[PDB]
Image (cartoon, coloured by chain):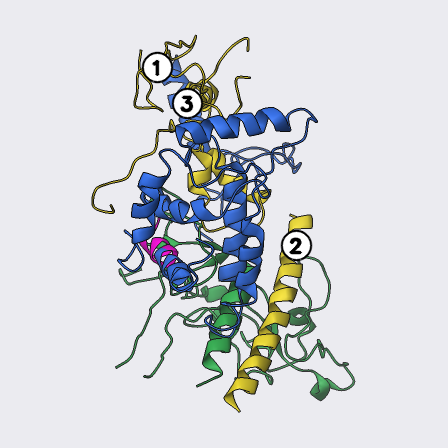
Amino acid sequence: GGRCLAFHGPLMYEHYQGWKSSWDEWVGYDRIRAYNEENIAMKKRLANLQIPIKLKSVLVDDWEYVTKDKKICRLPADVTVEMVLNKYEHEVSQELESPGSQSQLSEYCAGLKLYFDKCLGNMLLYRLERLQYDELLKKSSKDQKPLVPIRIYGAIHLLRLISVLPELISSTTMDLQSCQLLIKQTEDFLVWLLMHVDEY
Amino acid sequence: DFCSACNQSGSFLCCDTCPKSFHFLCLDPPIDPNKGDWHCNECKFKIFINNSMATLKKIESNFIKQNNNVKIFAKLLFNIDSHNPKQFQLPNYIKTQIDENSIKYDFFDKIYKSKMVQKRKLFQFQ
Amino acid sequence: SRGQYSDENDKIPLTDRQLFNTSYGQSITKLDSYNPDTHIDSNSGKFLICYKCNQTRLGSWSHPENSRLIMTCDYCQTPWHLDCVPRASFKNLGSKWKCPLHSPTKVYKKINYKVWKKQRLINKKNQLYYEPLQKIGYQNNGNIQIIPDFKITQIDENSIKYDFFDKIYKSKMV
């Protein structure tokens, strides 16, 4: 189909056109069109968005509170996001999600875990919290093991993380209905945490 | 001098390529200072991509062929070094082969969980 | 020739050699005389296997009535018997013979109605813009292509199966 479809420089392909039969080659390498290499280099140089107002008091309460206490005083924190992320597949996915595939919850949970795996160092880092992360990386470098933040970080910063993702969501070229779905599951998250006030 | 990632003054720290002022006790990369040289992440991607190589070609175009278990947000993962970090703030308004087996197993588990939620809904309907 | 619309749906006109002086037996028709050359493709010399029934049904010269007419598709070269799909004769004059297995140009979904006369493809210049981001619940209303302004996505088999199962798992309650 069409009139111009060639992996090499196009010669109105619909094999090297305009040449004899003793020049064919069908080996496999990388392919680039480049418009016949800029038309043989111009013929050899001419022949040479915000969260809804439902439970917004939490970040107001925690903005003043992290100035001197930072919401945590024990480095091996007993609160981990692993169980509260695992409970989503057993509590809200079996009740609120429409019958079908739970990919929109499980895949998003795995993506949130992957984002939390490397989100440290660039964002969500108060100054003394940065010092605490520095001392955690110092004490975790004595056995040349990777720093895994699933066992030393609480779930209290997850609310701030879903507060600070939407303005960097629109920082890249992205379709609007993906952001609509993002804010939809953010609304689902705040619906789930509306009555579960003990863990946060 | 100043700190773009601290919104303060602090001490003075300089860089060989793209010299910017930051805190000496808090390095811009996540690697702790507790060094012989310091290289910022914006300095890194610049000297790596933004100088003369693959400006038109998207590096993140072929990043999906090896990454698994993240699909919704992938363009923002590429430019994780192009933007410098900053201190805490808040606006006043608010105040493929193994991957094929992996996705096949995920679809298998999702089909079984669909069977379980079908059983749950016909149990709760009756 | 006179300045009419001519996309890939319409077949090229047949020449006078194939239409007037195409001998007697041939007569631009395979319904008459034994025509075993229509059952053999010149690309590989193998047998054209029909999609519905997996038989070429060439038959024998001693029993010409046991032979079944077959035709080659004009898009994917898929063989098809004349008795499986309801059709009397071949398709030589007019549009190209589109087998009933591809994407139709216009469909109807009565609910007044939506036509969706396809997008008839865009050339390989900068107008053809690709953006694969989301696989579940895109609502891209078609015009997709399969990989291993007019917005199109690089969809695969997994995403199609996912949204199909999602839609028929929401629709089985109604």
**Residue C155: horizontal and vertical position, in percent?**
49, 56
Q: CA distance from mark 3 to mark 1?
A: 21 Å
Disc 3 to disc 1: CB gap under 8 Å: no
Can you identify the residue that label 3 sits on? B42
Name the residue at the left extreme: B93
Q: In the image, which lettered chain appears green?
A: C
Horizontal side of B21 relative to B73 (left or right) equals left
Q: In the image, which lettered chain appears blue?
A: A
The chain under label 2 reads: B
Q: Which mark is residue B10?
A: 1
Residue located 67% across and 60% down the image: B105
Chain B tint in image:
yellow
The residue stretch that appears in magenta: A172-182
* Circle 3: residue type: Glu
Which is in the foreground here, disc 2 or disc 1? 1
Q: How many other residues sit within 10 Å of disc 2, few (<14), some (14-19) or many (≥20)?
A: some
Q: Which mark is residue A19?
A: none
Q: Earlier in the sequence, mark 3 or mark 1?
A: 1
Residue located 37% across and 52% down the image: C122
